[PDB]
Image (cartoon, rainbow, N blue to C red):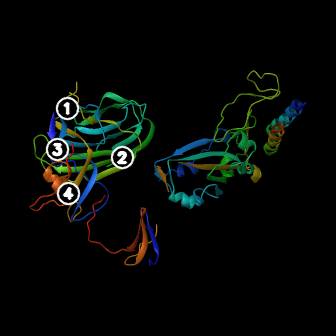
C-alpha cells in the first residue's frame, strides 16, 4: 500500500538530515509533497 | 447660561484667496447675535452640523476635546489633547472616563483620567483673560477641520465685541460619524477645584454670509444674510453699503 | 496654443523596517506588517533592498507613486530559491499550497533576494521551517501555525510522531554550501488595499502653458504676483 512506501521515503529524508545531507533531504521532501498530491 | 455671539464665528469657507472683494458663501456658520452657551461644567454637548468653541482662559484650563457618535470604545472617536510640547490628535477606539480630565498638581500635569482603551488606533498626530482662542470644528465628507484664531482681549467675562477671521488651522481625513463632543478641562487637584476660565459653545447652522475680503485676503467684516432686513438688503445688493432707496430682498409667504 | 504641459504637486513609510529587518519569519508563520498613515517613494522599489528581484502584478511601481490606498500590507518570510516562483498568482506547490498563498487576481508586488550570507549556517540553520503536510490547500492570505501531528494512515497518533504520524513542519536546515536553488531567499509581498497611504514638472514663467496644480487643470501664462495669499 501507499503507507509503507511513504514511511520509507519519510525515513530517508530524516536519515539524510541526521547524517548532514541537508540538501538531499530537501530533495526527498519535494518527492513526499508530490507523492501525496496524488490521489 | 447664554451669551450673544455678535460677529464672532466667521471662518474662511475654503482655501481660496479673494482680495478687496465681497463674497457670498452658504455654509455652516454661527448665526450673528445668536445665543452661545457659556460655561465657567463639561457636559456631553451635541456636535450637530459643527461646533464653534471660544476659550477665554489664562491658565490653559481647556486641555482638549473628544468627539464621538456613542462616546464609548464600541466605536472609534477623535480626541485632541494638549501637553504643550505636542497636541495629540487620535482617531482611535477609546473608553472615556465618567469625568475625563488632566489633573495638575503644584504646576505639573500628573493625572490623565481620560480613557481606559486605546485600541484599533486608526490615526495618531503629534503637532505643535489676555488670550481668546477660537476653534471651529466641522466634520464634513469624512474630513474633520479645526479653524483656530488667537485674540488679545481684556474683557473680564463673556464674548468681547469684535471681528476676527478664523483661519483653518488643521484638516484631517477622519471618516467617522461625530454626533456628540466633550471639552476636557485641566481640573487641578486641591477633591477637584479648577482655576478661573470660561468656554463658550455655539452650534453652526446653514447660513449665507457676505464676507468682505480686504487687500490681504483677510475677512475684515461679514454680513449674516438672515440676521435682519438691513442685512438681507446688504446681502441682496452684494454690497456692505446700500444706497438710499427701496430694495426687494425676499418673498414673504404664509 | 500652450507650448508645453507642467504638472505641480506638493514636494516616510517604514519600508526600511520591513526590508532591512534583522530577523525574518518562517514561511509557515509568515509575518504581516500593516502600513498606514504615511507617504512612500515607490519609485525606488528597484532599490528598496539589495540584489533584489521584483515583479508587480498590478500597475508599474511609478504609478504606485500617484496612487493612494487606505492600507498597504507587507508580508515577509524565508523560502528556498527554487520556491520563489510559487509566490505568484495562480501557482501550486508545497509553498503555495500549505504555507503562503496569493489569490489568482493578485495585483501587488513580490520582491525576493538571496539571503545565503545571513540565513545559512555551517551545521545548518534549523530556525526556518515550512509545512509539508496539510489536509487541504490554504485559501489566499491564510496562515496556519498549528503543529498537530499529521495522521497519514488510519491509526491515531495520540499526539506523538511515529510511523505514518508526521510532525507537520520540516526545517530547511540552510547551509552556505547549498546550491543557489536551495539557498534561502528573503521575500516581501506588498498588497494594496482600497486613503492614508500615498506615493512634479519644472515650473516655467511667462509662457502659455497647460498647468496642473494639485488637480487644478488650466491654461495660461504664469507670472510673478504681489498678492499676499493667506497660508491656507
Residue B108 shown left or right of residue C3 in the figure: left
Position of residue B235 measured from the top left corner of the image (x, y, whole percent): 19, 56
Gap in angstroms between the C-alphas marked 1 and 4: 48 Å
Viewer-proximal residue, C160 or B29?
Answer: B29
> Do dots 1 and 4 share one subunit?
yes
Residue A29, label in figure: none
Please state which of the two labelled residues, at mark 3 or mark 4, is closer to the viewer.
Answer: 4
Residue B194, label in figure: 1
Residue C227 shown left or right of residue C16 in the figure: left
Contact (CB < 8 A) between labels 3 and 2?
no
Residue B5, label in figure: 3
**Residue displayed at 53% across by 52% down:** C16
Position of residue B231 measured from the top left corner of the image (x, y, whole percent): 16, 53
Residue C57 shown left or right of residue C221 in the figure: right
- First along the sequence among labels 2 and 1: 2
- First along the sequence among labels 3 and 2: 3
Quickly name the residue at label 2: B140
Gap in angstroms between the C-alphas marked 4 and 2: 28 Å
Q: Tell me the chain of label 4.
A: B
Q: Tell me the chain of label 2.
A: B
Q: Determine whether the residue tagged by mark 2 lies in a helix, strand or loop.
A: strand
Q: Tell me the chain of label 3.
A: B
For residue B247, what is the image quadrant? bottom left
Vertical placement of C45 versus C99: above or below? Answer: below
Viewer-proximal residue, A23 or C46?
Answer: C46
> Do dots 3 and 4 share one subunit?
yes
Please state which of the two labelled residues, at mark 2 or mark 1, is closer to the viewer.
Answer: 2
Gap in angstroms between the C-alphas marked 3 and 1: 25 Å
Q: Determine whether the residue tagged by mark 3 lies in a helix, strand or loop.
A: loop
Amino acid at each position: 500500500d501507499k503507507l509503507w512506501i511513504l514511511q520509507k521515503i519519510y525515513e530517508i529524508m530524516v536519515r539524510l538530515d541526521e547524517e548532514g545531507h541537508g540538501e538531499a533531504s530537501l530533495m526527498v521532501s519535494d518527492l513526499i509533497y508530490e507523492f501525496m498530491k496524488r490521489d | 447660561a447664554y451669551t450673544n455671539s455678535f460677529t464672532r464665528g466667521v471662518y474662511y469657507p475654503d482655501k481660496v484667496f479673494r482680495s478687496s472683494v465681497l463674497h457670498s458663501t452658504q455654509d455652516l456658520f454661527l448665526p450673528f447675535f445668536s445665543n452661545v452657551t457659556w460655561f465657567h461644567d463639561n457636559p456631553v454637548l451635541p456636535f450637530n452640523d459643527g461646533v464653534y468653541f471660544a476659550s477665554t482662559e489664562k491658565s490653559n484650563i481647556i486641555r482638549g476635546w473628544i468627539f464621538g457618535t456613542t462616546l464609548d470604545s464600541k466605536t472609534q472617536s477623535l480626541l485632541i489633547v494638549n501637553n504643550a510640547t505636542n497636541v495629540v490628535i487620535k482617531v482611535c477606539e477609546f473608553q472615556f472616563c465618567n469625568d475625563p480630565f488632566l489633573g495638575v498638581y503644584y504646576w505639573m500635569e500628573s493625572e490623565f483620567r481620560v480613557y481606559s482603551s486605546a485600541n484599533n488606533c486608526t490615526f495618531e498626530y503629534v503637532s505643535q483673560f489676555k488670550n481668546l482662542r477660537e476653534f471651529v470644528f466641522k466634520n464634513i465628507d469624512g474630513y474633520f477641520k479645526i479653524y483656530s484664531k488667537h485674540t488679545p482681549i481684556n474683557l473680564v467675562r463673556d464674548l468681547p465685541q469684535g471681528f476676527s477671521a478664523l483661519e483653518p488651522l488643521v484638516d484631517l481625513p477622519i471618516g467617522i460619524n461625530i454626533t456628540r463632543f466633550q471639552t476636557l478641562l485641566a481640573l487641578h487637584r486641591s477633591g477637584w477645584t479648577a482655576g478661573a476660565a470660561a468656554y463658550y459653545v455655539g452650534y453652526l447652522q446653514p447660513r449665507t454670509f457676505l464676507l468682505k475680503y480686504n487687500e490681504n485676503g483677510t475677512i475684515t467684516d461679514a454680513v449674516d444674510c438672515a440676521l435682519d432686513p438691513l442685512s438681507e438688503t446688504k446681502c441682496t445688493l452684494k454690497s456692505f453699503t446700500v444706497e438710499k432707496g427701496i430694495y426687494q430682498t425676499s418673498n414673504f409667504r404664509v | 496654443q500652450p507650448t508645453e504641459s507642467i504638472v505641480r504637486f506638493p514636494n516616510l513609510c517604514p519600508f526600511d523596517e520591513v526590508f532591512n529587518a534583522t530577523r525574518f519569519a518562517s514561511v509557515y508563520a509568515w509575518n504581516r506588517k500593516r502600513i498606514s498613515n504615511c507617504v512612500a517613494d515607490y519609485s525606488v522599489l528597484y532599490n528598496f533592498a539589495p540584489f533584489s528581484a521584483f515583479k508587480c502584478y498590478g500597475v508599474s511601481p511609478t504609478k504606485l507613486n500617484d496612487l493612494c490606498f487606505t492600507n498597504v500590507y507587507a508580508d515577509s518570510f524565508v523560502i528556498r530559491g527554487n520556491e520563489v516562483s510559487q509566490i505568484a498568482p495562480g501557482q501550486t506547490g508545497n509553498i503555495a499550497d500549505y504555507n503562503y498563498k496569493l489569490p489568482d487576481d493578485f495585483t501587488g508586488c513580490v520582491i525576493a533576494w538571496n539571503s545565503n550570507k545571513l540565513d545559512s549556517k555551517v551545521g545548518g540553520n534549523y530556525n526556518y521551517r515550512y509545512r509539508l503536510f496539510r489536509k487541504s490547500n490554504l485559501k489566499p492570505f491564510e496562515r496556519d501555525i498549528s503543529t498537530e501531528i499529521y495522521q497519514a494512515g488510519n491509526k491515531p497518533c495520540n499526539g506523538v510522531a511515529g510511523v505514518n504520524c508526521y510532525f507537520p513542519l520540516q526545517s530547511y536546515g540552510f547551509r552556505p554550501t547549498y546550491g543557489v536553488g536551495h539557498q534561502p531567499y528573503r521575500v516581501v509581498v506588498l498588497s494594496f488595499e482600497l486613503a492614508t497611504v500615498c506615493g512634479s514638472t519644472n515650473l516655467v514663467k511667462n509662457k502659455c502653458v497647460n498647468f496642473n496644480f494639485n488637480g487644478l487643470t488650466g491654461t495660461g501664462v504664469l507670472t510673478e504676483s504681489n498678492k499676499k495669499f493667506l497660508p491656507f
